[PDB]
């Protein structure tokens, strides 16, 4: 299982190093049961693009940063891009993309509180 990471250059991947500074996220309520996922280190929001890539942006007006967190028992949740209907996936190789099949083995996350309001997004594997 890997921690979701938004790098300073805007790329998104996974990592097992919990000491990385780019895995801490601020989840800000948006209404509609929708939220934003903001990497506090760089001020970048998690974004799923319609083509399936995942990256970071500071553009708060961007429509692809809105997410729905959907609980799936056992502590796990899914993270769905509202605008494209894609679920966040962290692949075994460490790459991060979007998929529209809810049956995928790598789209389930466990949210881990850091103690300061910020949370880690860790893939269950």
Image (cartoon, rainbow, N blue to C red):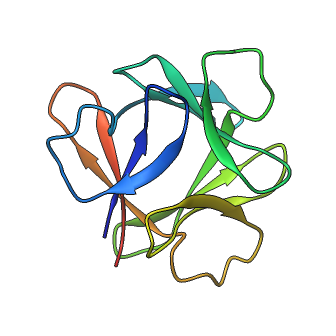
Q: How many marks?
A: 0
Residue at 74% across, 77% down:
101
Residue 104 appears anywhere in the view: yes
Q: Is residue 65 above or below residue 93?
A: above
Q: Is residue 122 above or below residue 48?
A: below
Q: Is residue 22 above or below residue 125?
A: above
Q: Is residue 17 left or right of residue 70?
A: left
Q: Is residue 116 above or below residue 83?
A: above
Residue at 17% across, 48% down:
18
Res 46 → quadrant: top right
Whole-percent x, y for residue 11 in the image? 54, 39
Viewport quadrant of the N terminus = bottom left
Q: Residue furthest front?
A: 9
Residue 33 appears anywhere in the view: no
Residue at 68% across, 15% down:
60
Whole-percent x, y for residue 35 in the image? 59, 33
Whole-percent x, y for residue 106 in the image? 51, 75
Q: Is residue 118 left or right of residue 77?
A: left
Residue at 64% across, 59% down:
97
Decide which of 35, 24 is in the foreground and name it: 24
Decide which of 92, 48 is in the foreground and name it: 92
Q: Is residue 80 left or right of residue 42?
A: right
Res 20 → quadrant: top left
Viewport quadrant of the C terminus = bottom left
Whole-percent x, y for residue 64 in the image? 76, 35
């Amino acid at each position: 299982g890997q921690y979701l990471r938004i790098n300073p250059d805007g790329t998104v991947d996974g990592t097992r190093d919990r000491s990385d500074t780019h895995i801490q996220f601020q989840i800000s309520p948006e209404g509609n049961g929708e939220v934003l996922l903001k990497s506090t280190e760089t001020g970048q929001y998690l974004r799923i693009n319609p083509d399936g890539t995942v990256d970071g942006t500071r553009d708060r007006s961007d429509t692809h940063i809105q997410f729905q967190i959907s609980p799936e028992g056992n502590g796990e949740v899914l993270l769905k891009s509202t605008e494209t209907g894609q679920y966040l996936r962290i692949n075994p190789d460490g790459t991060v993309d979007g998929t529209r099949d809810r049956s995928d083995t790598h789209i389930q996350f466990q949210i881990s509180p850091e103690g300061n309001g910020e949370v880690l997004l860790k893939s269950t594997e």
